[PDB]
Image (cartoon, coloured by chain):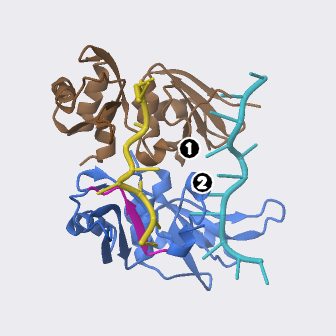
Chain colours: A brown, B blue, C cyan, D yellow
RNA sequence: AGUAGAUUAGC
RNA sequence: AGUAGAUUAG
């Protein structure tokens, strides 16, 4: 089957009223839910303002993301690809961005190589190979979910060779 | 439509210093087609650095090569391992040989057969141990699995996600009680 | 002494 | 409390 982590969305900005039951009845419009939970404060039992929805298939996850915007219990909420507990500890893991850093490209790698591999994740806006070639490049998408789909994957083969993918940064 | 290059690549450690790209190739193409084969050399001396990489066309061929250990290349037994990505190679101890993994993030209803059901596919299991807290009696949220061949572990840690009992869980090479307090 | 690729952070 | 799951080191 497909790994649980790839079938899970993080839902940001929940209302205090939002429950496992209310969250479920909304997001089950886009598929079957293997799990649906609001994270609550262990001591107060207040909602902590976010939850998780898990579909049976990644297709259903994709459908829910394609049906943005999402309003739950009177509140616009923010669904994003669920970053694993391990990757969540890395700085910038949770930023909403449209641009990725691509490092480890070989010297004969051209722009159409990068386009051929990254098209599958979403509409590409801009590709820029760094010149001085220094072995890295930048790709800009029009939808942050395109980036999120990319960084939850481990390997990326461009022109027959692995390369590392990171969210592009401000500093 | 291939399989990622990183999963098709083996690190070959301990090469004879006379081994070349071609001699390394003629040995390892006995187990399949090689999309690449290289001896790593020092940039200034051009001398061999004592290790290389071979990449097969399919991971199936990688498995065949690993199942044919030991491998003697140009008179010397070499040590082939799953090629750890440059990114993962930067963390301490990434290349140490272990048969035992730490498994963290298992739910309270996760049983011993759940762990065995998922990890069997990587190799013969020797020992599974779910950690229960003394003084409380219930599960602590992690476990340990011991395999019979380190390559089983190496095949596990080059994958990203591991769904045990319907939930993701993290896998790390196990360190000793001493090594951890440090 | 030894078996981890290093041209993987933009003007 | 209010947008990252600490029951993830024996």
- The picture places residue A8, in percent across and down from the top left corner, at 30, 38
Q: Residue at x 60, y 33 (%)?
A: A110
**Circles 1 and 2: CB distance less than 8 Å?**
yes
Decide which of B36, B170 is in the foreground and name it.
Answer: B170
Q: Is residue A6 above or below residue A167?
A: below
Q: How many marks?
A: 2
Name the foreground residue: A59 vs B52: A59
Of all chains, the one bearing label 1 is A
Q: Is residue B124 visible?
A: no
Q: Quadrant of residue D9?
A: bottom left
Q: Residues within 10 Å of mark 1 (few under 14, many from 20)?
A: some
Percent across and percent down for residue B145 are 35, 71
Q: Chain of mark 2?
A: B
Q: What is the residue that sits farthest to the right in this orientation?
A: B44
**Does the segment drawn in magenta span residue B72?**
no
- Residue B37 sits above or below residue A22 on the image: below
* Residue that numbered label 1 is attached to: A164
| Secondary structure category for the residue under label 2 | helix
Magenta segment: does it hold B104? yes
* Residue B86: assigned label: 2
Which region shows up in magenta? Answer: B97-107
Residue drawn at x 54%, y 33% as measured from the top left:
A114
Q: Position of residue A7 (x, y in %)?
A: 28, 39
Q: State whether residue B43 appears in this view.
A: yes
């Amino acid at each position: 089957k497909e790994p649980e982590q790839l079938r899970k969305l993080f839902i940001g900005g929940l209302s205090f009223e939002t429950t496992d039951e209310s969250l479920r009845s909304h997001f089950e419009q886009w598929g079957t839910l293997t799990d649906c939970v609001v994270m609550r404060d262990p001591n107060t039992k207040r909602s902590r303002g976010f939850g998780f929805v898990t579909y049976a298939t990644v297709e259903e996850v994709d459908a829910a993301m394609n049906a943005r915007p999402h309003k739950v219990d009177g509140r616009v909420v923010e669904p994003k690809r669920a970053v694993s507990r391990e990757d969540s500890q890395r700085p910038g893991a949770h930023l909403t961005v449209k641009k990725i850093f691509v490092g480890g490209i070989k010297e004969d790698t051209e722009e159409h190589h990068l386009r051929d591999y990254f098209e599958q994740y979403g509409k590409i806006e801009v590709i820029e190979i760094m010149t001085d070639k220094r072995g890295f490049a930048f790709v800009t998408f029009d939808d942050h979910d395109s980036v999120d789909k990319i960084v939850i994957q481990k390997y990326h083969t461009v022109n027959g060779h692995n390369c590392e993918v990171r969210k592009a940064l401000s500093k």
